[PDB]
Every structure is written in structure tokens, then in C-alpha cells.
Amino acid sequence: TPDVSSALDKLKEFGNTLEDKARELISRIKQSELSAKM
């Protein structure tokens, strides 16, 4: 196991970033699913 003492710390951060990398990114994903003029 990782640093068992301050390993939960990371998840209060790196998690925020995914809810914007799969929420704002999802709009980037919709505009790039044609393969016609990427």
C-alpha cells in the first residue's frame, strides 16, 4: 500500500479534476466523433 498516513489526501483533489475531465471534456468528445474533418 501507498503512504498509509496521508494517502487519502490526494483523492481530495485528483478527484475534482476528473469531474471536469469528464464533464467539460465530454463536450470536447461530442465535437470529434465524425472522423470527417477532425
Image (tube, rainbow, N blue to C red):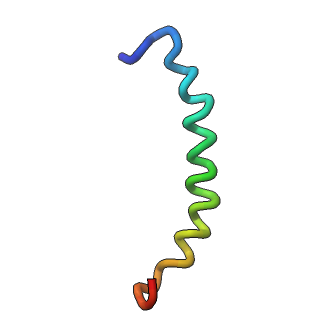
In the picture, the quarter occupied by the C terminus is bottom left
Image quarter for residue 4? top left
From this view, report whether residue 34 is shown above or below residue 5. below
In the picture, the quarter occupied by the N terminus is top left
Residue 35: give x, y in percent of width and height: 40, 85
Rendered residue at 47%/80% (across/down): 33
From this view, report whether residue 26 is shown above or below residue 2. below
Residue 12: give x, y in percent of width and height: 62, 29
Rendered residue at 56%/69% (across/down): 28
Residue 33 in the figure: left or right of residue 28: left
Image quarter for residue 17? top right
Residue 34: give x, y in percent of width and height: 45, 86
Residue reaching furthest top? 5
From this view, report whether residue 27 is shown above or below residue 1. below
- Count of number-bearing discs: 0
Rendered residue at 61%/69% (across/down): 27
From this view, report whether residue 6 is shown above or below residue 15. above
Image quarter for residue 36? bottom left
Residue reaching furthest left? 1
Residue reaching furthest front? 38
Rendered residue at 50%/9% (across/down): 5
